[PDB]
Amino acid sequence: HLQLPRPVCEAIIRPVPEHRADQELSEIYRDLKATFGVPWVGVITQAVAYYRPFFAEAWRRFAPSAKTHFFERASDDIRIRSWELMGQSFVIEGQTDRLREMGYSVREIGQIRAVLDIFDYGNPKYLIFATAIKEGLLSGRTFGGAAGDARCHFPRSPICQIDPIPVMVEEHHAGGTLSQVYADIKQTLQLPFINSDYKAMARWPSYLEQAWGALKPCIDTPAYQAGRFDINARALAALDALPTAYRMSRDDALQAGLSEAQTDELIQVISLFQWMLSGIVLNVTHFKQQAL
Amino acid sequence: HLQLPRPVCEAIIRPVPEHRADQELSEIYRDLKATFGVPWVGVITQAVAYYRPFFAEAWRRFAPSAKTHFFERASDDIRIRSWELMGQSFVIEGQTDRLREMGYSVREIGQIRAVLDIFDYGNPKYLIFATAIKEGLLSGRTFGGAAGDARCHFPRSPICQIDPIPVMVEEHHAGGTLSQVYADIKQTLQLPFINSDYKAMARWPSYLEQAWGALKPCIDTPAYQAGRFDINARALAALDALPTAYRMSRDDALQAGLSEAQTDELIQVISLFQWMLSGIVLNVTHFKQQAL
Amino acid sequence: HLQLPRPVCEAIIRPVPEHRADQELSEIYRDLKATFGVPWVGVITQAVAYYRPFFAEAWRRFAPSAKTHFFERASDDIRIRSWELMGQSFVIEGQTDRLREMGYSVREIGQIRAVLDIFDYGNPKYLIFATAIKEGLLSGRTFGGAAGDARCHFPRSPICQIDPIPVMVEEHHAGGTLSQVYADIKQTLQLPFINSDYKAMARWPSYLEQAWGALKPCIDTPAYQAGRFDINARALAALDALPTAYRMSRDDALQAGLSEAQTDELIQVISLFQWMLSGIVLNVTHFKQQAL
Amino acid sequence: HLQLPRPVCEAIIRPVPEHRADQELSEIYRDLKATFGVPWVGVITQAVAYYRPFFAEAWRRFAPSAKTHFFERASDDIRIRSWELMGQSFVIEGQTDRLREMGYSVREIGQIRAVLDIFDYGNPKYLIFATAIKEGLLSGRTFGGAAGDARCHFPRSPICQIDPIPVMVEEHHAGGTLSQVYADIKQTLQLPFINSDYKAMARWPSYLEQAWGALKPCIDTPAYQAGRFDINARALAALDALPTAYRMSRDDALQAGLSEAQTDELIQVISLFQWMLSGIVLNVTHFKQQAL
């Protein structure tokens, strides 16, 4: 009965997407993408972006760890675990053939796998970042900092795809039918937003409904909820193990320039996204397992 | 009341899309795109591609002209005329303010214009090609070939975007309301196919539904049907003025490897697509005037 | 025996290249590239950009004309004339067989032509811009702006290559012998700088060694000097026919924030690049006819 | 005083570069790049590619292992080991200060690092592949295949740079000084060819002049020599642990269609490249530490 609570969330989330970002924000957005080695700024960071002096300083405190061999391996090990959990817990009778029947060519199915690959690789990095932000605020604690194995502090595996931004069907791009797929997900996952993951799948409307439609019955089953706690506890372990110490408390929030009250709302906001992220990692894993 | 007849189109169309093309075909596809200087193979040429040795040979007979200063200016003057025609015959309200209110940012509206630019540039080039193919078959005639102004034989203005293929929501990609928006168009336009320019617009569903919604009432008004005659007449004039003579008769079809039967079917296919291309040139013009 | 008088420029040129440009200036560079529809910022515009508030202002005033059918055709008509001129004045030996025998493959020779095309397309546009800036300052006149044919004000031929920036071997990149070919070019062309064109061709040092060596004997022959004057005059004529009036005189330069002392230097600097731009249009034409 | 014996190479090496590779071979070249996740076909694979039916068959059999977490981790640990090794064996002064003073902007130095990054990531993967071909042929043995940890069989970390092909100044591109730096490199490393990485560094000839000059004294110091053997041993150990069994014996090479004469020749060619990739791994590690 291992299970992860969806927090209270009073808070209005105010993402700054990349197509609206001003030049100052877009610089941090670029540093973020380059450092992780991902071609998309996640909604979580679009949302912490609203509290921009916090985001700026938090990222600055976190960026050194993100650049390390340790952080590459820690994220990669969360992807592997998800691949392990979902393969053991759920039946994946594939869908390459289902897609062929629908009309999809081998080229197209390639392009889809390539999109799911991006998020497969990128989400454990956002999860760990989310975790550090939320736990730093909540506990005021200093995390990581140990020397240990010197190879842990080495530069991460260096190749990366950072351009272009994946094609994403935003919520105001959406027509009616797709809007209902988008409402169906928000409700099912209990989120006020559509993940970048689904939006990029949505470029292929008929493909997204098929995939989501196979994933939906697995959400909040006990094995899913167990698996999600597991993924969550591993991001908590990566937080404890950062190569460069990370502290960003409520008081560092004030010093960064936020009111006490804005810090309270930020905590609700990051707690929501942090809870979202262990779930999307199972979610993306599922889509990718079907795709093979 | 000048009108140009929608022909009979008994014939099944069988386009080989780029994501399906094999190595041999993809190579002619690359030469096509490179010469015209467009990043997409048009449905017209996808469809004539089914009759591959005719398509191969016809393209060979036409490409010398396509590479010329003459052909660049003839295509460009067709765009200019359509801009001229639609600007006068139609009151087209600006509508970027609507898009803004729907939630589209200044950057997104930019990307949308960039897509319309592609087709605004490329469709006169496909229109003239489809005209050469059609009339060569019907009349057996040898068109152009005059020396004239030596500058007409000069290399065309050199710059092109060749990549990537635009993002198109193909018909099997399409979801619910979009399959009915696609249906709406097929019917209104009397076509069995959805054009590439709509599919590219389809990446922004909400933007398609009401760009199209604004254009639909214009189709087959007298000023529309007349503007279309004008565009069709000008492609016939560019056909007569080709700097390298083009002949591809019915008997060349047979020589190419086609049967009498297949050639009969090809004539129906090219006539339908040829008819389509003057309509789509006004259509794209309309979209693009809306988007100022 | 006709020729373009080389101006005297004692003035130091201080180009801001794209790889040192700050955010604000990159934003203007970007807009310049998107409107011209070329992938590179000219050394001409890099040197004017030093006197930044004047550059910013000459560009806002000129850009309305740059976006027009008139400006696209006028620039393109200068490319045609240079092709005509060099073709009739010079017997140019083909060099692709000699490239082949040096080791160059078909694709490579193709890459070489593609780069040449970029400058064959772009440079007349810079020539006209430079002419406008120079004459506006020398004469104080308002140029163009007559109503005339409505089509001249239409949007220009709409698709372009903006990315990536051409691979250019800068002077501080060059090793010994490439620094000697750069020295040669400078003295023969009478310039204190290396054009973007040669640096781009310099990606293939041996090809540049060849194409420059075949061009050089033709430099400042009578047929060159007369053709150059004619190219020049075409730019001056392009100036009087601009769709949207352009005035940027000394009084305007002062108002933009320049001193008296900086305006005299700017007049010198633009004067030297203006003279230059007639020569580079012919030079790449020779290049490009060598490579047929 | 440990050292890797250089093998006698009598054989003429005959690489098909990406810019000459035909359609069939380019499609093998593609798959190799999309599996390794690098944007370049290595010269080792270019030379084995001459023996094309053997090349196709050795890659079909090795590709199952290359697609695995094991292979990703194992290649990555070779990168980690060389960093560790050159770091504790050598005190390497920074060079970015001299690059600055030479004229290199912050972005250019950034670009150079990004190119170094590529090889830093890819080369271990080419080391291991080359090791499998050499040992397979020399010993007739089946390599890897034991079940072990299930995770080893999982899909590798799923993101890559596959385009564009790095800018590489080939030997028929090079001019005067470059040819002599290339000459220096060949004799110093005892190779009758230039590696992809020096030709890439060569886009910036003065950078290559500087980075190679700082390396060359270190070449064949005891420390270098001893470290190179270690890297070589770990490749040999990666070979015994391949997730999916690999056999490609001389007998196998006969079935693929090689004579006995070509197989002797192929054994000499792969042997010389096999020896070489242990060195290039240390070599670029050095450049990269020079450039921190």
Image (spheres, coloured by chain):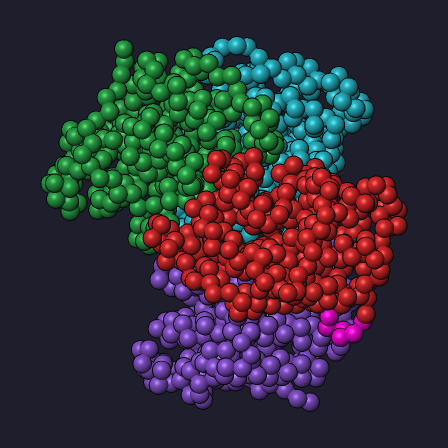
Chain colours: A green, B red, C purple, D cyan
Q: Decide if residue A272 is in sight here.
A: yes
- Is residue A79 one of those drawn in magenta? no
Q: Quadrant of the C terminus of chain B?
A: bottom left
| Count of number-bearing discs | 0
Which corner quadrant holds the N terminus of chain B?
A: bottom right
- Near-viewer residue (D262 or B63): B63
Q: Is residue C35 left or right of residue D60?
A: left
**What residue appears at the point 57 percent right and 87 percent down from the top-left corner?**
C5
Decide if residue C254 is on the left or right side of residue C151. Answer: left
Residue at 24% x, 45% y is: A50
Question: Which is nearer the eye, C276 or D284?
Answer: C276
Residue D28: x %, y % from top left: 66, 33
Left or right placement of residue A191 versus residue D212 in this view: left
**Residue A170 vs residue B263: left or right?**
left
The vertical placement of B159 against A32, above or below, is: below
- The span shown in magenta is B147-155
Q: Residue A268, percent across and down? A: 19, 33
Q: Nearer the viewer, residue C19 or D153?
A: D153
Residue A135 locus on image (x, y percent): 21, 29
Where does the image place residue A199, in percent across and percent down from the top left?
41, 37
Q: Quadrant of residue D36?
A: top right
Residue, x 71% and y 75% (percent of image)? C84
